[PDB]
Amino acid sequence: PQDLSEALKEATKEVHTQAENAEFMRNFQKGQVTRDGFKLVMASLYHIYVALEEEIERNKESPVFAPVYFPEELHRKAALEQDLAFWYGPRWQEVIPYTPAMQRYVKRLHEVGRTEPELLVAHAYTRYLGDLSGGQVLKKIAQKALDLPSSGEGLAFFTFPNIASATKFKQLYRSRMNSLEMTPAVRQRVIEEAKTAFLLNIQLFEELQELLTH
Ligand SMILES: C=CC1=C(C)/C(=C/c2[nH]c(/C=C3N=C(/C=C4\NC(=O)C(C)=C4C=C)C(C)=C\3CCC(=O)O)c(CCC(=O)O)c2C)NC1=O
Image (cartoon, protein in one colour):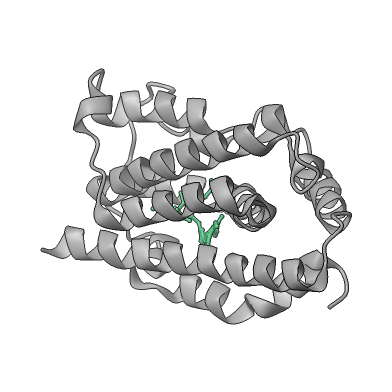
């Protein structure tokens, strides 16, 4: 559907729904999340965002990504470092898990950023705007399900400090993404990569649930 954002929304409708219906995610949404479950999602995000930001930095000047380069408004690496220090302690870096599901997500991010940068937009869009859009709801759900201590740390990931209005930001981001010049072949691959992004998350949810039970 003409605008890239709309074509993405239509093509990923099924996989997006499946991501929401995935047991671990479905449960998180229903308020059924444990401290162990929550810590794993946080470790996962840390790995994903380290990888994504590394590739964004490498391709920030390229006309195939520049329009969507918003370093100050969206970077999450530092927020996640801050959160992990609280969830895993001062030695979090050497104690956080790094499972195969997380590894294959990181792997794809690096493949894209290194050889197919024109597809990096698909991951940035789905990861950043998805996290930005549902951050406030999952934050609250976690607050009452986790029963955190009043130490003012651990949930910075859910707050984008340099974005005053999420609604106006997403509008600017969408406009910038729709502004990208793409040949027919390029576009179809970006759409396919968007599906890939949702599928990597769905596989991650499956593994996290598996680790919790077993
Ligand atoms: C390409 C990126 C991408 C996909 C496919 C993803 C899907 C996705 N992320 C979600 C939220 C979420 N799911 C968890 C986390 C998990 N969720 C993850 O995508 C990852 C990688 C973890 C880590 C194990 C958290 C913390 C949120 C809220 C994200 C936020 O608002 O900061 C849910 C519901 C969000 C809502 O009520 O708030 C879905 C279906 N979101 C996206 O941004």
